[PDB]
Image (tube, rainbow, N blue to C red; front, side, top):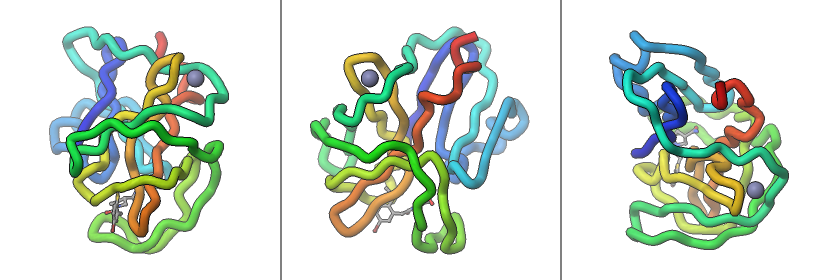
Length: 139
Ligand SMILES: CSc1ccc(Br)cc1CC(=O)N1CC[C@H](C(N)=O)C1
Ligand SMILES: [Zn+2]
């Protein structure tokens, strides 16, 4: 689990959104596994606006933050799970690292701020849903 809190927005994995996030929906995209809902309180996360390919992510299944190299956002085939059938997920970045289903939501950060959140994984890989292209999160 986990979320990004920027301005009056809450960014979570779409598959983990609560009935309350859907009522306060701003934007969602099943193909990106992202949902953004409105908040009453102002958030303090800064979103990165960069092309960094190295960063640090939080892995809740290890209670550890790991430095990683990750690929640029791309369209990647993602195996079936209890939340989606087998499909291509867009704006996804992969890294070699540990992840379990409940790690989704953990933040990936570079020197510029938040890059994205854990969204996919398994077999020694971890995938992150990029948020750096969502320029509107800043206004
Ligand atoms: C970090 S996700 C993960 C990790 C290890 C294993 Br094995 C399997 C997973 C995959 C997983 O459960 N999902 C849920 C939905 C998500 C998606 N974005 O399609 C992928
Ligand atoms: Zn950066």
